[PDB]
Image 1: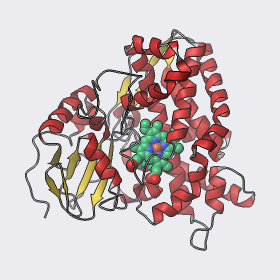
Image 2 (image 1 turned 120 degrees about the vertical axis):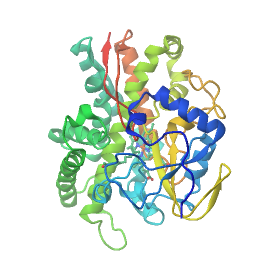
Image 3 (image 1 turned 180 degrees about the vertical axis):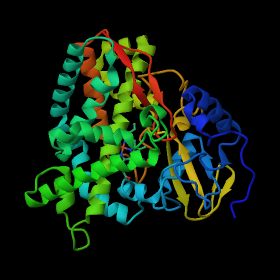
Image 4 (image 1 turned 135 degrees about the horizontal axis):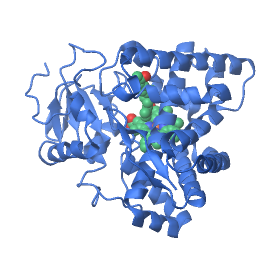
Amino acid sequence: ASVRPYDTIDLSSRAFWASSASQRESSFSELRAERPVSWHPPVEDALIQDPNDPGFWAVTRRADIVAVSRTNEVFLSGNGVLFENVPAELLEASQSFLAMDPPRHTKLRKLVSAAFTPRQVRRIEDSIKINAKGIVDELRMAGGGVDFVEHCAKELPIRTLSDMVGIPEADRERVAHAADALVSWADPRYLNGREPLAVLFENQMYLHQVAASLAAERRDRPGDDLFSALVNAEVDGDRLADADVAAFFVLLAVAGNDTTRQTISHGLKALTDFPSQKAWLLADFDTRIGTAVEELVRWATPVMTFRRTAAADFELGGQLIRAGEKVVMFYASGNWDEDAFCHPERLDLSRSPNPHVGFGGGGVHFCLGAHLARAQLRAIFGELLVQLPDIQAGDPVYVPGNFVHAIRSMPCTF
Ligand code: HEM
Ligand SMILES: CC(=O)/C=C/C=C(\C)CCC=C(C)C
């Protein structure tokens, strides 16, 4: 029946998700301490209001986030993974195997998983380094005071993504813009008065146009790339339908662009806010970039929320989650868990171990592009230190929303 008192702490209002991350942490802190698994009403003023939705369970502790992520046989992804209620047509055209359970998730992920192994990322790491060098070079020619997001943070992800999938150059900047749009539906500075559902469809429609054109191109002459193997594979005795192919292209475009782009912006600001941490990394880069990248991901946590649906009754945090109830993981709360980290509010690029859940709590849906993301962050931050040793981030403009911890724009000086 899902009938129980709602928690006192507000995790659903628009104003809560339009406030600073520090303000939200004071709410996450009390929950982590007193009621780590709490019941809340659905996200207010959602893209679609669902009378079938009684609420959700808030999972704030890192250990519990790992428990939900790894126990996928109980906490399913096949009934949706987004925190806010989103119209089904928009979900069906974007989620792909992210919102899928085995065995179908195992089938589809296997078709593209070969291009993300550490071996294959090492094979293409030089091209990422070459793109990072030219991007920082072009940023230097732009001069100080320019927007770091548009002139750097968004450039390396789309170049790395498009090089793997084979996106035509004329479509590269529009795909990056369309991918960023699909997580900015709560940003008035992005909508600019437009109703969000129409903006989401328009950008989804364009990405499906690029997907249909690339799928038809690769079915004629297949290549060694990621999209070639997907559109030419035989799944259950037949090639994948156009809807499945386009949905994965959206998933790949959004996850491959938005997450790394925000981590780069958050990383430059973190290096500016902690100069002694930047000097520590610079003093021995090749030996220390590994743990530094892991903490920059922990510091950014670009994916703030992902949800699951309980397949059966499950006891978590002293609370009996019922079958069919929504369970939301708050990765920013888990990465500030005092039960897991020593002073998580301070940037420590030497943090070891770093059991952060920036790539999720681990398990079946663990981030497909984790090795690729790490290679991008190592390359772009090494080039920013090679070419622009005095670079500093300005005032960031944070994007309101309950899904991605995003910076709309941020000037930089050097
Ligand atoms: C750089 C290129 C990236 C690509 C191509 C990529 C792609 C993907 C894909 C395809 C999935 C779905 C995997 C599945 O459902 O089995 C996924 C999951 C995920 N990704 Fe990534 N991603 C990238 C970077 C990142 C970064 C930098 C972060 C965070 C710092 C991130 C956070 C996540 C999270 C939280 C999940 C869900 C994990 C879970 O549900 O357990 N991604 N990614
Ligand atoms: C409105 C809309 O289309 C939402 C699309 C959301 C995704 C394609 C999920 C992206 C996956 C990540 C960021 C790990």
